[PDB]
Image (cartoon, rainbow, N blue to C red):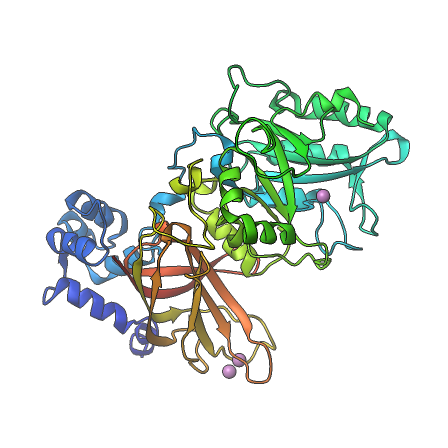
Length: 513
Ligand SMILES: [Ba+2]
Ligand SMILES: [Ba+2]
Ligand SMILES: [Ba+2]
């Protein structure tokens, strides 16, 4: 029993099976057999002895098998539960993309009314709100500045009862955390309602506090395009109105001149300058995407566009970012403080490219001569249908969503495809009753995805309730090109984006053209 029970608890058939298939009759996987697994099952492109051997050196527990270039079932499991066994590509968990193009070519992690911790009407504001966001990799922040007592500018939500904070205190927090998560440029959106004098104060604080991090002069030779993330590495840049407004501030706006949306031109008239940025509410954006989908896309190739949540979302709720990304919208601002599927998708996207906060758009979204319109799909390089098969096998140590600490979870799994409208889909498994430790579903879903470059696959686990809304247990969102094949574990995250140390899903993924 102290083995029976013990090791029976700690025992997974699906794993046994997998090893068996891999290893066949042997009690061990030889480097050769492992390589075959890595290739045939895991579809690793760098599949080979070098890979195999590192996996064994890295994960094999038996000194004998290790020394002898072999993997036991235990090392097999370790591997599968490791960062290498993660359904989210380990290789993409480091900056690996081209960081030398104009900013407008990247999707940028952006926050809305960053200072807020809760609702838009009366909740608190705090420097913490800025620290958190920056710690989640956010690059684009928002400061709503108003005149404050003692000639000290404050920040809060204009015309509301939201609590207040100091512009200067905010600046220090930003300075301290701007690059804790990424070395790439941070952009500060200043919504300026300050008197001339206090505007002067702001400028003083900016210079004093940010010091040399602040970008206050154009980049040398940057003439026809926005600089690249690499060129602006380690810098903070301001976005706002440029010449009611003191020069001290206006002179600091370099590549992000706040501008009213004109329309989409083409030549050197109308469709704004690269160093100028327009903003669109959630609604206007949709309509524009609705009527002038390709115009927007094309507009977005050389220009940065900021989207922000509809005014009615006083609860700080969030819209779906995907719909904006499909149009090439880069600065899609969300309420970082609000847990939900929207932020789940948001942070899944930005976990890519080493989580640096700048994720390179697909090529077709970087072609000024683009005929793409996610809303009216025609043939083009973006069209590359794939057949995805996901098998939800089992779950391991699913957290109790909390509740009257006595009931046991009755887990079910939902799998969703987010992307161009035609690709969006969702499927769910059955509910296993009373088992969060090791529910087993062994259910498979298949999805057809025509524009994978814009897709994301999301796994969600709920605790089923007949009497009410199901409790969210954990989640994980993976960008299409980071989705690893074969047998893998999906490491579940909490509402708040936190990693759940031992809560996982064991799955088998296969992608075929
Ligand atoms: Ba604002
Ligand atoms: Ba129960
Ligand atoms: Ba329940």
